[PDB]
Amino acid sequence: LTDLPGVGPSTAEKLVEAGYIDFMKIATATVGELTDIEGISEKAAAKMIMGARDLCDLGFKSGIDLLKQRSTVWKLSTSSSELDSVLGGGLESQSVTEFAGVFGSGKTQIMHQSCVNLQNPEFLFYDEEAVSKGEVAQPKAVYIDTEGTFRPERIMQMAEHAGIDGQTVLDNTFVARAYNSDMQMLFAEKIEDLIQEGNNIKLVVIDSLTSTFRNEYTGRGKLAERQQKLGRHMATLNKLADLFNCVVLVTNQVSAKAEQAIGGHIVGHAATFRFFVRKGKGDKRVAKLYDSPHLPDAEAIFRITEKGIQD
Ligand SMILES: Nc1ncnc2c1ncn2[C@@H]1O[C@H](COP(=O)(O)OP(=O)(O)NP(=O)(O)O)[C@@H](O)[C@H]1O
Ligand SMILES: [K+]
Ligand SMILES: [K+]
Ligand SMILES: [K+]
Ligand SMILES: [Mg+2]
Ligand SMILES: [Mg+2]
Image: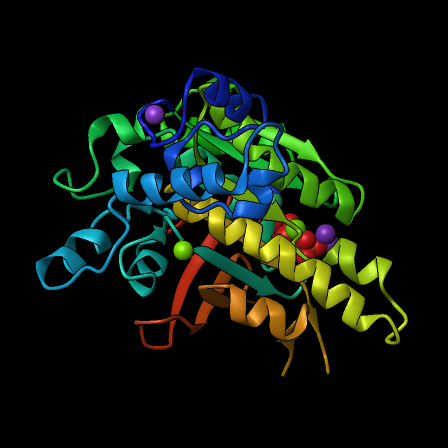
């Protein structure tokens, strides 16, 4: 912290107490959020922000540097060959990928499978030149369970079939049972603390993303209220994915209104990748990518079995 212009040992102590220890956290802060701290003046706040942006070299980039920035994105396999292909390799870090679909389509299964796959080094695809082995070492997941459907037994079973130690996954996966949108958002905001505590959070799951909000802001005369709160939550999720270079996954429910993911416009804009998961015959499922910034729409066929997601 004292490497930052204007920051002395006293100021550093204040910055850490307020949770600002990472250079990126400071480089992307506002004089306001910084001035809310004790003896941190506006000139001081401003100087350290500029310094941090500088140290993190956050300026104009062109040419090959654009490819290099894009190479810092690593991807997590879904265990499905077709889904990984439709995703352009796998689930992208630094982005929010949404899986929406009818009940039983497998949204929660995908979330569990991802927590298991995170513990298999061979399922994290990345360019060694842009992402070092250390950056993805001892990765951990955060599962924010909004409906109470987290199942340790499923994690174990999926792991065993993958040749992974079930307990190992449980030991490296943090679960937070949120009973409402307030807890849901607060937990998401506290993921920073788990990292500050030395936990390499590389996967964040929000299952479900919208169920709490829909139940709390029913009267369509309070819809604006809902969209606003939901928007702050999405922003927090997007920022955390970028700063901590981890993949963020969210599940969403659907309405008839042939259907559409709930959450309205705010969710549509904030989600980087959007899927619609359908049920085929028996254990067959179909994930339809219908929104992404660089990939074409496509469908991936897979199955949900005792082994989890496969094919
Ligand atoms: N151990 C298992 N063996 C085989 N199939 C399983 C197993 N566990 C779950 N499934 C399948 O997973 C389906 C449910 O998956 P689930 O992830 O809960 O869907 P969902 O989209 O999250 N549902 P919802 O949250 O209500 O909208 C089941 O109905 C089973 O067919
Ligand atoms: K300094
Ligand atoms: K259900
Ligand atoms: K459910
Ligand atoms: Mg991003
Ligand atoms: Mg579910």
